[PDB]
Length: 129
Image (cartoon, rainbow, N blue to C red; front, side, top):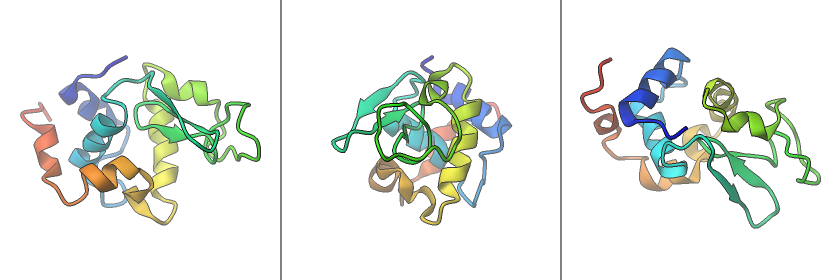
């Protein structure tokens, strides 16, 4: 599922992401656009052998399990394929544990390079919230 802009912001707000760890809603929506372009089935291979999954591109080296990343951890205790569902519930709960891992939102290289320091509020433009 390729979410709509204001459609995805509503589902993230319902799942408790707005101001989660002090990060406004426009930040999370900004990170989605620049990690997966709002597409739930996005996948990208990394150079070290791991793979990013889902609407916020969660890495298999540490968080989920794909059975093909040797020496990996499964911190979110889920199959990485669960991060590709039309329901972002699994991706939201796993990202809550990522942003709480010390470095904050910096764990998403796209957010730090394309969202951090910008007018993130412009991403919830005209959304019925």
